[PDB]
Amino acid sequence: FVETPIPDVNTLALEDIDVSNPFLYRQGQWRAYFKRLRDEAPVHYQKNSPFGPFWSVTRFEDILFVDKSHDLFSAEPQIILGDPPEGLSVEMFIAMDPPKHDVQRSSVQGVVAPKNLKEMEGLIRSRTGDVLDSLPTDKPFNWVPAVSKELTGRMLATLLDFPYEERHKLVEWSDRMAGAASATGGEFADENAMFDDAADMARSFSRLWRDKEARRAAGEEPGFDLISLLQSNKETKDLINRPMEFIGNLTLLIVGGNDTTRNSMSGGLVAMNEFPREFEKLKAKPELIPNMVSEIIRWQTPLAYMRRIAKQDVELGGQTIKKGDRVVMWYASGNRDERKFDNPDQFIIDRKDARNHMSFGYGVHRCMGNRLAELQLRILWEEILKRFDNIEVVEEPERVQSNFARGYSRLMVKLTPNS
Ligand code: HEM
């Protein structure tokens, strides 16, 4: 993939609108392209793309139907638009249908048990406050590494009890995975690097499993982390011996929580910068933080879509999706659908229906980590409000190349503390 200027959507025949282009978000053309699809081709077939042909489903109501109807639309074998590079396919329950999906999700869902998240609030808030206190207030800095990636990486390490000093690896491996050119149009096109990483990652999870079992056998009390949970349950105490399940489950937790958390933490600042009256509203009414977090997640939509395959011919939106066709559920478009949300492109932190967004999906795959993400975002903004009278974005944000992740690689921020 090489970036070129994306033309006005009005220059295109409807059949030539290709929303798999991974520069549509960066260039700001995604809003007009998806509005044209919602209005005039809400169930749209693209015959020609670098990823092969695919349907786009772009209205909120129709996306709900596809996401909930796993008897008609399969999540197998992959949920990104393209294909993983050869040798890198791993089975993850995000790309599995019931009943097996339900079985595999049950084996890990305890890691985000509400009682466990509540016990970790002090740690999350301490990390958040320490990170914010460390930021300079006399010069701008890049928020993406300093805050969003920093906090996400610590959280991911805690979730796995992954060696804290190596947490940068959970994220580097994960980035090169979720950013495969063949899968998402991301910038990673070297299969040699992905082979090195996927193997390093698999070896690292195996060493962690053995270190944790040796520590448990030696009398270490079990913790909140996923490995401890897997080793405490009869069904999964032997998960090492099922390598596809073991590697797939652990990889899904890390990839699932990595750039989603990161880009939600960054995106709230970008939304405030575009709608600065909302920050004055927030400072005057801090009890809006929980609803604001929903509005940040709606407006940002950190994952633009999830993909499905039609299990049979399905009539949708005056169109016949054929058995075997790839069907892309464009959450990024659904969350801007004016049939669902009034003034959808506005960031409105007291929007009463913000919580009804589809950024987590709907149906059996609805995000397992939704409460953990919301918790971290709430604490982030609580701790921001204690410290800063103003936040300024000093340069146009740099947006990531991807058709899947909607995110930022550079967000240059100047802080003004209160007195
Ligand atoms: C604001 C942040 C997040 C967003 C926007 C998001 C988005 C999503 C989406 C769109 C799906 C699939 C929904 C569908 O197909 O219907 C999903 C599933 C999933 N997410 Fe998240 N996610 C976020 C945070 C997290 C975090 C923090 C974690 C882990 C700590 C996580 C782990 C997972 C897992 C394991 C699944 C698979 C659930 C299943 O297939 O049953 N996510 N997420």
Image: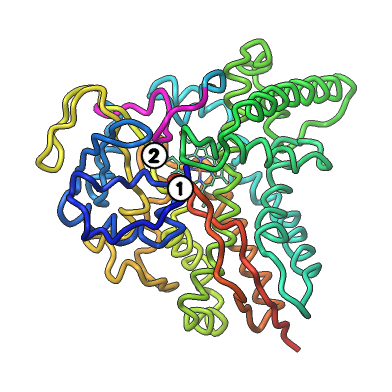
Please report contact status of discs 1 and 2: CB closer than 8 Å, yes or no: yes
Q: Residue 162 placed where, x, y %?
A: 76, 35
Circle 1: element type: loop
Q: Is residue 352 left or right of residue 213?
A: left
> Does any atom of ligand 1 lie closer than 8 Å to the CB of label 2?
yes
Residue annotated with mark 1: 303
Mark 1 is on which residue type?
A: Leu
Is residue 75 inside the magenta stretch? Answer: yes
Crowding at mark 2 (Cα within 10 Å: few <14, some 14-19, many 20+)? many
Residue 111 location, quadrant: top right
- The label shown at residue 176 is none
Looking at the rendering, the stretch of residues picked out in magenta corresponds to 72-85
User: Disc 1 versus disc 2: distance between alpha carbons?
Assistant: 8 Å
> Does any atom of ligand 1 lie closer than 8 Å to the CB of label 1?
yes
Circle 2: element type: strand
Q: Going 68% across and 53% down the picture, which residue do you hit?
A: 149
